[PDB]
Length: 261
Ligand SMILES: Nc1nc2c(ncn2[C@@H]2O[C@H](COP(=O)(O)OP(=O)(O)OP(=O)(O)OC[C@H]3O[C@@H](n4cnc5c(=O)[nH]c(N)nc54)[C@H](O)[C@@H]3O)[C@@H](O)[C@H]2O)c(=O)[nH]1
Ligand SMILES: C[S@@+](CC[C@H](N)C(=O)[O-])C[C@H]1O[C@@H](n2cnc3c(N)ncnc32)[C@H](O)[C@@H]1O
Image (cartoon, rainbow, N blue to C red; front, top):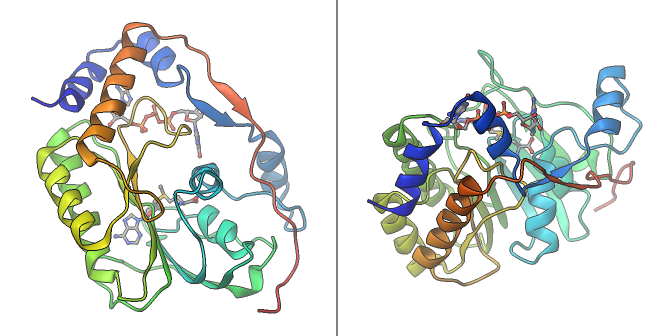
């Protein structure tokens, strides 16, 4: 019914070569060569990012969609790309990252980029069931892809519901993955959240064309339906005319060392 739903149905119809060409068409990618080299080598003294995911938060932060300040919570931190990014930022006082890190899920990677000493990771932590805590900046990058649109809807709704559960009165800043934003139930939920909390939704250019993921953020106000439909139309247009070529950008590099505050 929605254009996003049309997009999702059509993505599954793509043969191998068409899918591979499509997913990278006109997207932005960070060059992960240096980071992969030092990660393989096992170095902790080079200011690399532990994941490709750090590129997404850098973009959101630098483009002004998200202030990162105070006590930061990183829900579903995985390797910790968003946690280390946050820890290096001027106004950040501490970062707490929670993740499952069990049964095939990514474990936090120990690194010594700026502010590593103000980061605390806990694995074996299910953010859907564990007790909440206050934060000034609440990050959540959770949303596992599925070819079943109903599974993506359910996963998205659980993330948005858990976000409202964790969000405290002092949580003025936030960034939450919205895996499948086009689903009418998800649009409705986002609209309700926006009534209470403000903010808006944005497509991060580092996302592959094979996902409709968008981020619900605190730093900009916009029209949810319009922003979602604009991304759906963009994804559909890229499908009709796939370039098969990504724009390459420099990776997220950080200083190394401890911080006092
Ligand atoms: N290994 C690795 N790669 C990273 C990373 N970051 C970016 N990449 C970049 O991702 C590319 C491969 O795509 P990836 O395997 O990571 O996931 P893709 O988008 O294929 O698929 P996925 O996100 O897992 O699934 C999205 C949806 O696409 C659809 N889909 C997946 N595979 C296929 C397919 O084979 N055919 C069709 N028609 N649809 C598919 C399904 O609907 C699925 O729900 C890499 O070459 C690299 O440039 C990283 O941290 N690790
Ligand atoms: C997309 S990755 C996060 C990437 C991260 N932002 C980065 O830059 O490295 C999502 C992570 O959330 C974790 N996760 C999924 N469900 C979770 C849950 N219920 N509780 C805690 N972590 C969860 C997954 O294991 C995965 O490692």
